[PDB]
Image (tube, rainbow over all chains, first blue to last red; front, top):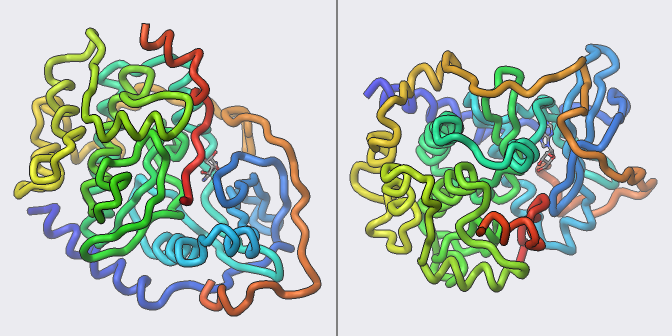
Amino acid sequence: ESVKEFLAKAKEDFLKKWETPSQNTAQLDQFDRIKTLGTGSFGRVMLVKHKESGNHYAMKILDKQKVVKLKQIEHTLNEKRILQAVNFPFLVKLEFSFKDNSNLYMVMEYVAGGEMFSHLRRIGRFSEPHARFYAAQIVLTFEYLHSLDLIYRDLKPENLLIDQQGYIQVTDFGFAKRVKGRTWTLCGTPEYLAPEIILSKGYNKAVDWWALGVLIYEMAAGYPPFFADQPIQIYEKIVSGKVRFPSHFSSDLKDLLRNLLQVDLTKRFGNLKNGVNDIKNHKWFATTDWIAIYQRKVEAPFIPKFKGPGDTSNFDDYEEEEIRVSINEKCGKEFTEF
Amino acid sequence: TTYADFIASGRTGRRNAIHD
Ligand SMILES: Nc1ncnc2c1ncn2[C@@H]1O[C@H](CO)[C@@H](O)[C@H]1O
């Protein structure tokens, strides 16, 4: 119950910032644009320098227009709202938000370890132990997130940033929604998508549970349990609920996955009575000190290495596209509350 | 090998999210 007690204070805290969110906390002029750190479906993430403090940050830039044409208004407002309110060790910290004629911005804490992905891809696979360590932190993160009526919707190695201490940082909240009850938007990353989503059934918190299981699998095996060259081909597999585990997985891991990768909601771990505790209590997580993990007192099995302040060596190289600002304020009514 | 199958595949790079 130290949890049930902890979250209580968590909730209270979230509620407040949720009702009274932060608006226009800065201006482009205070920032020095360095390199592109990465890309997403709605915009780019650049490495930034804060002139006066001398701090570097990752800055999420969105083009008012693109968001509109792609219909991401609600989602974009959702992301800043929710982000500016949460507070957990495994989620990125947003520091400044603000807009201008042309774009929307989100200044976040710069996580230099680079993406989980890049490392995952390089190394090949993760030792179940190395996996667990990461898992465990997503397990805790969902626990917090969910208790706030929040739904993540985009877990994928590409969104899991490795920090100076080799701990996770979940970035990109663009599909995260505060929602009591069912939701219906079709969004996410194909490989991670839950069946209920594809099938357009209306879905809940449990989708986040399925992605966890896809995550653990991609972590420990080297590939996703459902892959093909076109998303469609992927979809058919997901709804197929037919999964092959590598000969190298423990009977334990298999067990977990089978339950997370459950096509049936009234049967999928995470969505049951005991809720999370079905997961946390799993034999797989037998050697897990949830506290130490939370406390960031655990054994970082791997520590990316950062040369200096503003080192973009754990990130790929991107093409640079000049960001401009219209002398005409665009799409202002749609973004009143940003 | 599946791994073998995965590497030749078209989605080994960074995966974009789907709007619609
Ligand atoms: N805080 C951050 N630090 C560094 N790179 C980030 C950060 N947030 C997002 N990114 C990058 O931009 C992409 C946006 O999803 C990420 O996959 C990553 O490449």
